[PDB]
Length: 389
Image 1 (spheres, rainbow, N blue to C red):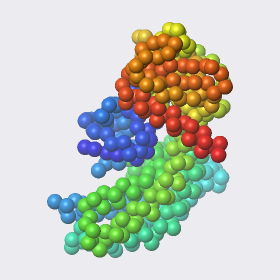
Image 2 (image 1 turned 90 degrees about the vertical axis):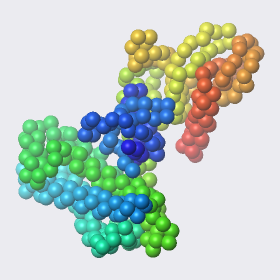
Image 3 (image 1 turned 180 degrees about the horizontal axis):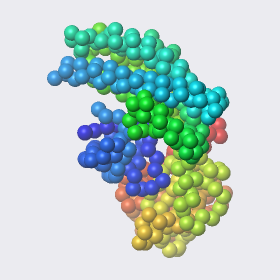
Image 4 (image 1 turned 120 degrees about the vertical axis):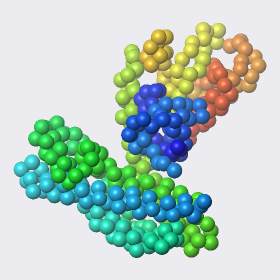
């Protein structure tokens, strides 16, 4: 099998296979229901199946017309179950839930339901029972394009429904209550906070489902230019929703990571920074004639902290310092022999202070890594430029 990262899966640990939206991983084994081992070209690990999208020709398109019609009848039953079992009971229970609590945890979820019935209704009209592969559906998306914007208001306040859901879950009253409703509407053994997560999950699923329908769709197909037309529109609304969601998450995994680093000296990282750019293992000389230390480098926007692995507990990292990139420039050294300094070089570059005569030498192993790095530095500057600007 082969899937595609829908979203980044940032991880404070090295174990978890980390990746960016688009990275394609190869699935080896899927013993678990919601946990499978992924293999990448150089990286390897286990990823969350919930954060990824699975992948003659007419038969392939027809299959496409069917899964889509099915994932939506599925997604709607979820909405029905959510409002019928969860929202309808909370309102009745004026004694456990205020109007404020209800708006916070649910929101316009009901509003999205109304939208979905009619969007489902129009699609079922377009489906071709005789020859499923002729289903002209591209348009159905194109006429309901202005409705999908209600989702953005649901993504903004989603994390506020989780905080109020985690606060109520602590009480045994709300536990049994939430466990009681889940059993009445006949839902799987997934909680409430996970169901409230399906809408924020489908709006994204839409773009991939469409791309897949465009590969097995031919150009003369009366639907072709429409299938291509619906893909684009959605995409914008999905980016506008993310960029918010990708950026917001990357702040918890940082402070989370900083409390893991031993003997941390200095101000917290989020005081000046708020985004990590690139990390790896490189050899570095603090000053000319100095001793070579093997350290693991972390390149943030505005700064770069360096640490020292525990020799036996490889996952253990000691804090050994940090470099301010605002004052430093990245001199790209050429192989051969260095001037005192006075060492020999292979895949090395340099960091020169802007006002001082301060200099630091770095040594990667592969050329792939000196490139990735020198590209990582070009990235942290455009970001501070893009940020400050």
